[PDB]
Image 1: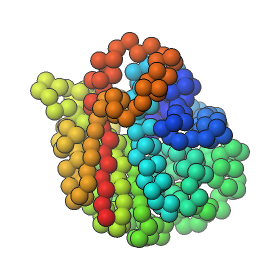
Image 2 (image 1 turned 30 degrees about the vertical axis):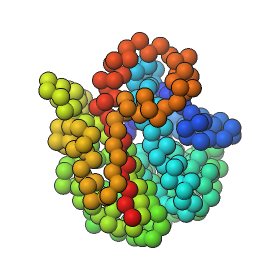
Image 3 (image 1 turned 180 degrees about the horizontal axis):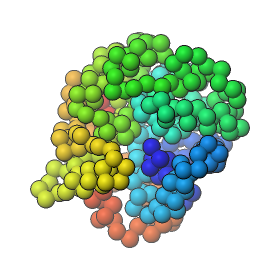
Length: 321
């Protein structure tokens, strides 16, 4: 999760984010997008010297190619969310594996009838609860008090926002949490940003079939990497070796779902499944005005190196009713 936060703060410091066109942010909410994430880094220092040390040095060692990958990852997920929230005013979002994601701050503001539900491991949501309650600007955005006033499973439960500890590998614990914070009939958006890659095939497939069957109308926006379908494409072999040799983590279903078609077949129950890798989103969805703006920030010397990386990431959008 500290990798994901290092990417977002490096993109904001250079200028890549916020993109007020694609994210549909106002003048005040564009300023607040920068001020909320900056106060998340300063407050993270107060609560952890080790976590601030890894996030600070990763920010400053960020390359232009990696900043283009964070831009497409953020405005890609945001473009799918905002199209669904405009067509449907009463919606509830369930951000599975949220981490340090702060997209609920501008989205709750922009949509009065929007509920939101951050869900992550116990350790991740305890640090996120400490940062939102400590900072003054993050407190005012969610209307929180400084103390831990919430009860039982929820660390936060103020108005139209809910932070909750939950083992997503456990399906019995996942459904029981969704019974108390969501309703069956209300349109839903399920975001799995960098979650299903770290899970085995049994835990991920049961999470997809159970949540889709729980709600009537919805839209699953899942972002993840793929191993690569071409022969002699060892991007998936390099990343699996880089994860264990670094901090002892795994990506069990990387080589299994090595293409955008195989990844999209997990949501085959849903009748409307689209899927496009992040290089296709760079050439199609991103306007010409936006690409000129990113060129003014940094020198993208190796555009082919950006294509090799971004074709090994995807954005799936399943929709059922």
